[PDB]
Image: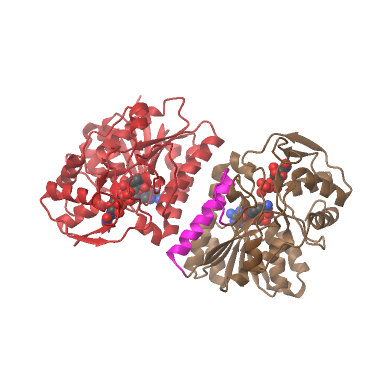
Chain colours: A red, B brown
Amino acid sequence: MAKSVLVTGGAGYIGSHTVLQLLEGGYSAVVVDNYDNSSAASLQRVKKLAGENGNRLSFHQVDLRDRPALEKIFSETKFDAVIHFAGLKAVGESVEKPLLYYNNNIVGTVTLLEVMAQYGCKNLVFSSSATVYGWPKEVPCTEESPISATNPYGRTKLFIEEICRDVHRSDSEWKIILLRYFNPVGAHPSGYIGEDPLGVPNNLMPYVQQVAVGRRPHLTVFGTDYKTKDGTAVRDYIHVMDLADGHIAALRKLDDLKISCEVYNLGTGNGTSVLEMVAAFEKASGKKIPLVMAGRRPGDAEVVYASTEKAERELNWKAKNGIEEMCRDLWNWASNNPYGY
Amino acid sequence: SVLVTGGAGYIGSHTVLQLLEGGYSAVVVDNYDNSSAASLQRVKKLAGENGNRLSFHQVDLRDRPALEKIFSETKFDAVIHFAGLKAVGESVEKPLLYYNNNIVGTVTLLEVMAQYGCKNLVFSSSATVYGWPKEVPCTEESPISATNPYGRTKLFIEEICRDVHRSDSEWKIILLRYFNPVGAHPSGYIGEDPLGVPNNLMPYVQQVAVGRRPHLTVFGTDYKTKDGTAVRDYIHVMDLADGHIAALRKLDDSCEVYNLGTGNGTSVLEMVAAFEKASGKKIPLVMAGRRPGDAEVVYASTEKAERELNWKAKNGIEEMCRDLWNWASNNPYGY
Ligand SMILES: NC(=O)c1ccc[n+]([C@@H]2O[C@H](COP(=O)([O-])OP(=O)(O)OC[C@H]3O[C@@H](n4cnc5c(N)ncnc54)[C@H](O)[C@@H]3O)[C@@H](O)[C@H]2O)c1
Ligand SMILES: NC(=O)c1ccc[n+]([C@@H]2O[C@H](COP(=O)([O-])OP(=O)(O)OC[C@H]3O[C@@H](n4cnc5c(N)ncnc54)[C@H](O)[C@@H]3O)[C@@H](O)[C@H]2O)c1
Ligand SMILES: O=c1ccn([C@@H]2O[C@H](COP(=O)(O)OP(=O)(O)O)[C@@H](O)[C@H]2O)c(=O)[nH]1
Ligand SMILES: O=c1ccn([C@@H]2O[C@H](COP(=O)(O)OP(=O)(O)O)[C@@H](O)[C@H]2O)c(=O)[nH]1
């Protein structure tokens, strides 16, 4: 009855929130994470938040590149599907440390895919990214549109998608959904869990949260010469909880027989600038964010936001939270957990 | 002093020989997936007095401890990275294998290189990174897009190399896009000796010619070419080898790309006929559908290499097939 899901990277931001939705949705979930960018605390708190559904969560501290540890996981539990969140995701770090990114992201993915194939679990939901749209010629960005990458991190997402496409062409038994996330922000509304990266955050809103509570001295704004309304980059910010719910919608979709290797955007379809996000955070928090204005971050797009039509139609899913809610819940988490777990 | 990955293989072996004859020292790592030690035993002997400057070891590039031991024992001035799987058709059926072997091995290799402060690299890329070209000849700056997993591993590895160079300008990297090497050392003492069922055209032909396979299967006869078969840029392997010596010299003044081809297109049937001319043997053919992932017409622009490496291919098809036959007839079961 109760379907069993392995969640790589499940102790991380998106993963932790999604694990909780899995548990509240009736799923059993086994998490695999090496705590490279997270801690044990997140799943401890997910377990509590999940109440009696907490029983259905197991967790192992395993690197996906550890084939023997991973085979062990797959030998002992019959997984209905895998959600693959595990990886490194900081663009800036990626340009500086490309091999770390190729190593962790591609080697960890290939090893997972081989192990899945060996133990007969060929249902995959992959954490892809709007970065694969590169510098879009046209917005909104549709699943049909041209893909490219502009930095090493983005290439790992692009290359993995391509690998999944080849795996599928090679072997018709695979069912794969490539979810292209836009920019998840916010925290579970209880404020008991949220984003807590190790060391220096590379995403905008956790960096802002950390300036707000006093742990970083300023936000650096990467680019004020964009051809946008305020000169800063425009992106599609989605509530992490809506993004989590999208994963429950993806898992239901794997039962469709037509599914072979399919792409869905998970975004809101609305574009918000960097300064609008900062303004919205200042509103929610009552705090000032000191800004240092700098140049473009190498590889950044100007304007990127989602077409939501395909996900609405085929997944029956649409984001329900606006920016104000995103900032409200982020601040609710951070005010009481200024330095994370 | 040069580390040669996949040096027991076809192109590796010939290149290692040229390295030894040109005064270099060579360490070879190979996991003998599509070769044996025997090839290197013969290069050593063929290399004469220079032979004692060759050393070789059974090592998988994915075996990081084994590969570190190698780098810890010798300071390398450069690496030449030939190791990998290379069959377009195999790759379509077995993508994870190709991604596992080609990418995990390369990534591991590059990390160890950096760890041990050897940041000079020549890489075996491929014309398959041009996918199905919309214009020929294929120029280094023409569009890069693969149509199969093998091609993608090559394309991906190029991109990883660029990123590596961008992250750290101490790296000097040359990406050689080989077209279709064929032939053998003109002595006939070394040549292509793949293990397992051959995948490439000419080792499949040579094995049909000596009784080891019953027929050659021709992959596609409805292409938009003179005789209906796919057209490639076949290049003598000794020419290719010499190109790598020139690449090593070029490293001493970047992440640069160079085609190594002849710039002439030859169809599959023309290659068979050239081989029948050289060998006197008749090759039974079975005509079949297109091989998944195959381009139609691929050939090289030779300008950039000529201009920048002072290198041109000098052997023709006729010399490629003679040398091939010379090796085949004297080593019908290879090594
Ligand atoms: N956050 C975003 O804005 C965004 C946008 C698009 C795509 N994504 C993708 O979503 C996924 C999750 O993102 P997140 O925001 O939750 O990041 P995160 O860093 O919180 O989550 C990643 C998790 O993976 C773990 N991990 C990393 N490498 C691992 C390995 N080799 N073995 C095991 N565990 C490993 C980390 O410790 C962490 O818990 C990533 O793949 C990321 O690329 C994120
Ligand atoms: N037409 C062609 O032959 C052609 C064209 C373009 C590019 N290339 C590339 O040139 C290189 C050499 O081609 P070749 O014709 O000499 O092939 P080959 O199979 O004869 O040589 C490859 C060698 O690599 C070794 N090897 C494979 N995986 C290894 C691993 N993980 N660790 C260590 N050694 C490993 C094999 O055992 C073999 O000796 C390859 O990277 C191939 O993709 C070849
Ligand atoms: O410290 C930071 C982090 C991000 N950004 C900008 O905020 C937007 C969102 O960045 P993030 O890295 O979170 O998302 P991405 O678009 O890279 O997935 C982008 O335009 C970044 O240039 C910024 O100005 N400062
Ligand atoms: O048994 C074979 C092997 C190859 N080929 C064709 O001969 C050419 C050379 O292919 P090969 O595998 O040698 O190299 P590739 O061009 O894929 O690098 C291509 O058109 C192949 O389709 C063929 O018809 N039969």
Q: Nearer the viewer, residue B263 or A88?
A: B263
The quarter of the rendered structure image containing the N terminus of chain A is: top left
Q: Which of A192 and B220 is in front in this view?
A: B220
In the visual, does B202 lie left or right of A185? Answer: right
Residue A290 is situated, as x and y percent measured from the top left of the image, at: 17, 59
Residue B28 is situated, as x and y percent measured from the top left of the image, at: 64, 64
Residue at 78%, 67% (x, y): give it. Answer: B46
Which quadrant holds residue A244?
top left
Q: Is there any visible trace of residue B166 in the rendered image?
A: yes
B150 falls in the magenta region:
yes
Q: Quick one: which residue is furthest to the right in this view?
A: B280
Residue A272 is situated, as x and y percent measured from the top left of the image, at: 25, 45
Q: Is there any visible trace of residue B199 in the rendered image?
A: no
Residue B137 is situated, as x and y percent measured from the top left of the image, at: 65, 52
Residue at 21%, 34% (x, y): give it. Answer: A51
Q: What stretch is highlighted in magenta?
A: B141-169
B240 is higher (above) or lower (below) than B276: below
Q: Which of B127 and A14 is in front in this view?
A: B127
A283 is higher (above) or lower (below) than B292: below
Q: Quick one: which residue is furthest to the left in this view?
A: A286
B86 falls in the magenta region:
no
